[PDB]
Image: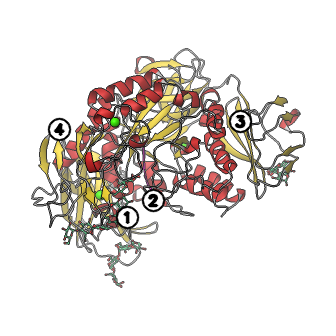
Amino acid sequence: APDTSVSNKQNFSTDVIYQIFTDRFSDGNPANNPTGAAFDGTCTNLRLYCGGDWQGIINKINDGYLTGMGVTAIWISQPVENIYSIINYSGVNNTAYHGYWARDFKKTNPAYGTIADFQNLIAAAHAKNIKVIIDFAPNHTSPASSDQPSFAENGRLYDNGTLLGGYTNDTQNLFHHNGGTDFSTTENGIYKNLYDLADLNHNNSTVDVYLKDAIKMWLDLGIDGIRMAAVKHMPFGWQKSFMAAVNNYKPVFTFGAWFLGVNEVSPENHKFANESGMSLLDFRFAQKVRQVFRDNTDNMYGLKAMLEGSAADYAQVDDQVTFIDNHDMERFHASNANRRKLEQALAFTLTSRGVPAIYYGTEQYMSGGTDPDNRARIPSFSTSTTAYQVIQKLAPLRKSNPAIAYGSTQERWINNDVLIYERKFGSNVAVVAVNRNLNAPASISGLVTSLPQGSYNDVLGGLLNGNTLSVGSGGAASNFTLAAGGTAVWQYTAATATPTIGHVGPMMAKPGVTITIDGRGFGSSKGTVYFGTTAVSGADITSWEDTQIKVKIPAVAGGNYNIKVANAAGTASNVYDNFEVLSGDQVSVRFVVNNATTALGQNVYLTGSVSELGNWDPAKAIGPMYNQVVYQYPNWYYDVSVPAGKTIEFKFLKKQGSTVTWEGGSNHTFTAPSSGTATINVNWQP
Ligand SMILES: OC[C@H]1O[C@H](O[C@H]2[C@H](O)[C@@H](O)[C@@H](O[C@H]3[C@H](O)[C@@H](O)[C@@H](O[C@H]4[C@H](O)[C@@H](O)[C@@H](O[C@H]5[C@H](O)[C@@H](O)[C@@H](O[C@H]6[C@H](O)[C@@H](O)[C@@H](O[C@H]7[C@H](O)[C@@H](O)[C@H](O)O[C@@H]7CO)O[C@@H]6CO)O[C@@H]5CO)O[C@@H]4CO)O[C@@H]3CO)O[C@@H]2CO)[C@H](O)[C@@H](O)[C@@H]1O
Ligand SMILES: OC[C@H]1O[C@H](O[C@H]2[C@H](O)[C@@H](O)[C@@H](O[C@H]3[C@H](O)[C@@H](O)[C@@H](O[C@H]4[C@H](O)[C@@H](O)[C@@H](O)O[C@@H]4CO)O[C@@H]3CO)O[C@@H]2CO)[C@H](O)[C@@H](O)[C@@H]1O
Ligand SMILES: OC[C@H]1O[C@H](O[C@H]2[C@H](O)[C@@H](O)[C@@H](O[C@H]3[C@H](O)[C@@H](O)[C@@H](O[C@H]4[C@H](O)[C@@H](O)[C@@H](O)O[C@@H]4CO)O[C@@H]3CO)O[C@@H]2CO)[C@H](O)[C@@H](O)[C@@H]1O
Ligand SMILES: OC[C@H]1O[C@H](O[C@H]2[C@H](O)[C@@H](O)[C@@H](O[C@H]3[C@H](O)[C@@H](O)[C@@H](O)O[C@@H]3CO)O[C@@H]2CO)[C@H](O)[C@@H](O)[C@@H]1O
Ligand SMILES: [Ca+2]
Ligand SMILES: [Ca+2]
Ligand SMILES: [Ca+2]
C-alpha cells in the first residue's frame, strides 16, 4: 500500500484531522441520550449532554460532509465510560459530556454508543478512507474528594465492571494524595491532581498493567491513532513505557496535549516530543498563528521565526499536530472579525509542515469564548462556506503533493504582512503566498522559487484572491501583485529519481517490530534498509513499493540509529535520524536515591548499563530527578522506562550544566521486573 493509504496508522502527515467533540457534533441516536438534569436537547446549557454520538459521526461520514471537505482523519472525544454523576459546581450542573472523566477504560461511554457502535464507526470511517484517532486520558479518573466520598463518584475506577478502588480509603494507593497542582513546577504538575481530578498513580502495578491492557483493547478495536491528554501531568518515564507497550504490540500514531502559552518555548516540551515515543500538539505553532493572524501581536517575522525554530527544535517536526484553536481556547473566529483571518490561518495550517487538525465547526465560522462557550453544537453542515471550500481545495494536496506532507520549509519572500514560503520534497514543490494585510496589496518582485519554468494556477482558484504565477528560468517569478488579504498556492509534482525518505514510524520500538518508511523514489523492487551501519534486506523487509516500505527492526543493541534506505540499484537515500531501538519490552521503574545533597542549580541524574539509561553517557543521563512531592530533598526520585527482566547496573550523578560528579564506589545493581512496576531505593555513594 502507498504512504497515503488509510491503512497507514504510523503516518498522519498526508492527512487532515477533523477534531470532533462527539456530544456536540451529531446526535444520530436519540435513544442513547442521557436523561433528566444531565441532558439538554436544545444544547443551550453547554455543560450538559446534548446528544451527539457515534451514529451521528457515522452519518456525517456517510453523507459526504467530512469527505466532501477533504477530511481524512478524525479525532474524537475519549470513548471510555465516564461517570454518570451530575456535578454541581457552585450552582451550576456539570456532566462528563466531554468524556474526560473516565470511570472504566475498558468500556464505552453509553451516550456515545456501544462497542458495536464503535466498531461500526471504525468500519464506516475506514470505508471512506478516514482514519480514527481517540482521545485517551490515563492521567486520572474523575472529580473526587477523599474527605467526602459522596461527592460525584469519588473518582472510582472500574475494570470492565469490576471496582478497583476510589479516592476515599485508597489503601492500595491507586491514586495520588498530594493535593492539587498549582502548575508551579513540572514535578508539581505531575504528582498532584489536575483540578479536583483523582490522579492515577502509575507507580501502582495494578494501575500500570490495567491502563496498558486497556489501550490494547482499543488498538484491537482498530483505532488508527491516539491523542494523549495532559501529557505534562504524567511521569515522562511512564509514558515512554506506555508508548513502548503500544509500539511493541500494535503501533499507532500518537500525540500528546502539552499546553504552551503565548510566546512560550519549552525545551522540556521539545525533549518530550523528541524522546517519549509520541509527538505533540503544536501549541508553539498555534499560538504564533493566533498572534499573527488573529490578535495582531506579532508579524510575519515572528511566524518565520517559529517555523525555523520549530524545525530545528523538534527531531520530527512533521509529526507535530498543528491547529489554530481547540476546545480549551477561545474559537479563532471572533464574531466581529473579518472572516479572511480564519481562512488564511486555515490555508496556512493546511499547507504547513506537521499534521493539521481542524476543530469541528471552524469551517462554519463558529465563535465562542473559553470552556464551555467554545463547545457549542455545530450550527450547520453547509458545504457552501468559503472556509469549507478552502479546506476542500487544500486538504487533498497533502495527499497528492509530498512536499506539503514531508517537505522542508523555506521563506522565499517576507515583510511585516507578507510571507511567501516554499515546501520541497524530492522533485515536488509547493509555494504559498499570504498577505495578512486586509487593506493593502503588496508588490511581489524578486521572488525566487524551486518551481520549474511555467505558469501556475492558484490551487485555491482565486477563492482567497490568489493569482496565477509566472515562473521564468532559475525559478524566478515575474512581478505580481499580492492582493490585500490575498492567499495563493502554486504547486508542482513529479517523479523523484532518488529514494527519498519523508517519514518513519513508529520512532521507538524493540527489534522484530515492523516500522513504516514513507517517501518517494523507493522503486518497485526490494532494496536495502539501514539501521545505522546494519543492513537489512530480503525477508525482513515485509513489503516494498515506491512510496512505502515495511521492515522489521533488526536485533541490534538498544540505542539511537539513523535510518536510511537504498533502492535495488544501490542508490542511497537521505538519512532519517533519531530512531530509538529499545533493549526489549519496557517496564516503568521508580528510582530513589537517598541523601544526595546538592548545590542550588545542580541536580541529580540517573545513568546505567542500558541505552534506556543512556549507556553511562552523562550527556544521555535521565533527569533531572525530582525531590519535592513524592520524596523530599535530599532524597530524589524519578520514574524510568527500562527493559523488562534485565539485570541493570546504574549510578547517580550530580550535574551542573555539562559538569558532572559521579557517585563513588561500585555500581548499583537491580533486575527489572518482567511486568508491572518496581521501586529501586538506594543511598547516594560518596
Ligand atoms: O485535606 C484537604 C483536602 O484535600 C483534598 O482536596 C484537594 C483536592 O484533592 C485537590 O484535587 C485540589 O483540588 C482543588 C483544585 O486544586 C483547584 O484548582 C480547584 O479546582 C476547581 C478549578 O479551579 C475550577 O476552575 C473548576 O474547574 C473547572 C475548569 O475551570 C473548567 O475548564 C472545566 O474543566 C474540565 C474540562 O471542561 C474538560 O474538558 C477536561 O479538561 C481536559 C481538557 O479539555 C483537555 O484538553 C486535556 O487534555 O485534559 C483536560 C483534563 O482531562 O477536564 C476539566 C476538569 O474537569 O471544569 C472544571 C471543573 O468544574 O472547578 C474545580 C473544582 O471546584 O478546587 C479544587 C477543590 O478544592 O485541592 C483540594 C484541596 O486542597 C481532598 O480531596 C479533600 O477531601 C480534603 O479536604
Ligand atoms: O522551578 C523548579 C526549580 O527546579 C530546579 O531547581 C532544583 C535545583 O536546581 C537543585 O539544585 C535542587 O535544589 C536544592 C538545592 O540544591 C539544595 O542545596 C537545597 O537548597 C537550599 C539551599 O541550600 C539554601 O541556600 C536555600 O536556598 O534553601 C534551599 C532550599 O532548601 O534544596 C534545594 C531543593 O529544595 O532542586 C531544585 C528542584 O526542587 C531549577 O534549577 C530551579 O530554577 C527551579 O527553582
Ligand atoms: O565500555 C567500557 C567500560 O564500560 C563500563 O564502565 C562504566 C562503569 O561501570 C560506570 O561505573 C561508569 O564509571 C564511572 C565511575 O563509576 C566513577 O566513579 C568515575 O570513575 C572515576 C573515579 O571516581 C576516580 O577515582 C578515578 O579512578 O577516575 C575514574 C574515571 O576514569 O567515572 C566513571 C566514568 O568515567 O562509567 C563506565 C563507562 O564510562 C564497564 O563497567 C567496564 O567494564 C567497561 O570497560
Ligand atoms: O542570491 C540572491 C539573493 O537570494 C536571497 O535573497 C532572497 C531573500 O532571501 C528573500 O527574502 C527574497 O527577498 C525579498 C524580500 O523578502 C522582500 O522583503 C523584498 O525586499 O524583496 C526581496 C526580493 O527582491 O528574495 C531574495 C531573492 O531575490 C539571499 O537571501 C540573498 O543574500 C541573495 O542576494
Ligand atoms: Ca444520542
Ligand atoms: Ca498526574
Ligand atoms: Ca529528524
For marks 4 and 2, give the CA distance.
36 Å
Task: Examine the image and state in which quarter residue 57 appears.
Answer: top left
Query: Residue 10 at x, y = what percent?
Result: 45, 32
Q: Secondary structure at mark 3?
A: strand
Q: Which residue is mark 3?
A: 430
Q: Which residue is mark 1?
A: 186
Q: Which residues are magenta?
A: 255-259
For residue 160, the mark is 4
For marks 3 and 2, give the CA distance.
32 Å
- N-terminal of the pair, mark 3 or mark 4, is 4
Count of numbered tags: 4
Question: Between residues 66 and 448, which one lies in front from this camera angle?
Answer: 66
Res. 571 in view = yes
- N-terminal of the pair, mark 3 or mark 1, is 1
User: Vertical placement of 599 versus 506: above or below?
Assistant: below
Q: Residue at x 65, y 37 (%)?
A: 390
Q: In the image, what residue type sits under mark 4?
A: Asn
For marks 3 and 1, give the CA distance.
40 Å
For residue 268, the mark is 2
Task: Examine the image and state in which quarter residue 230 appears.
Answer: bottom left
For residue 368, the mark is none
Question: Between residues 610 and 585, which one lies in front from this camera angle?
Answer: 585
Q: Secondary structure at mark 4?
A: loop
Cβ of disc 1 within 8 Å of ligand 2? Answer: yes
Q: Secondary structure at mark 1?
A: helix
Q: Residues within 10 Å of mark 2 (few under 14, many from 20)?
A: few
